[PDB]
Image (cartoon, rainbow, N blue to C red; front, side):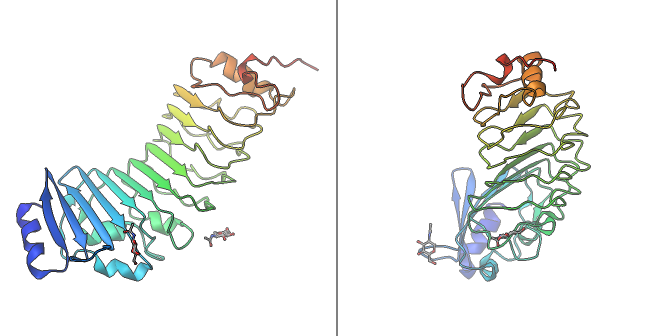
Length: 272
Ligand SMILES: *[C@@H]1O[C@H](CO)[C@@H](O)[C@H](O)[C@H]1NC(C)=O
Ligand SMILES: *[C@@H]1O[C@H](CO)[C@@H](O)[C@H](O)[C@H]1NC(C)=O
């Protein structure tokens, strides 16, 4: 585990400087640099933040060596690059970060397309947040083996969602897919979700949803569908209008119609 003694040792060799600030530790890599490659914030056994400023993936050599942070709950990686075709878990391993419950990877400088390999050796993760302003295509295998995952947030201007994205992810409790550019939803995307309580599909580009999309969401408590250009023509909006009327208590905010602006829940489709 990383402490005051481990922090003191770093300020002798000169590779990286450590400073005991408040109840945590601020690590600057390289030490004495105006614009450091790494800015680490370590609050022992609780939280570890990695503030990056890399021109290329090669700069990961500037990371503190022989560092043994140990067990940490939350890991926040801001502006960091994917270490090529190597898992993000390697950066965690190099720093001695053991069994993280949460991982937040926010970066507009990824350098490449996020693959299943970047998320490898992270099957024990409970919470995962991946944010990028850049146009990102998500593969179907990306979240495989992430079976212990209960919270997932993906804000990446994603246009299409692969159908087998949540294949063998039954422990999921919360999904945040807000402020993406999603036009569609696959038919059996939320098939095996017996533990999902919260689902956020707001601020997307959804005109419709396939019939029965939320029927297998038995544990659902909250749902966000607002700020979507919902096509409220019948019989297309029937399932969603009926579902949002029956599960009005679950709806957070109000999903409105493209033309009128009337809540989707207030639309009553006829039978023909
Ligand atoms: C990142 O590093 C470059 C030099 O490579 C520097 O010009 C820039 O100001 C740095 N940015 C931040 C936010 O530190
Ligand atoms: C990611 O992959 C897609 C094809 O699946 C490609 O069109 C896109 O340009 C790639 N992204 C980057 C940043 O190269």
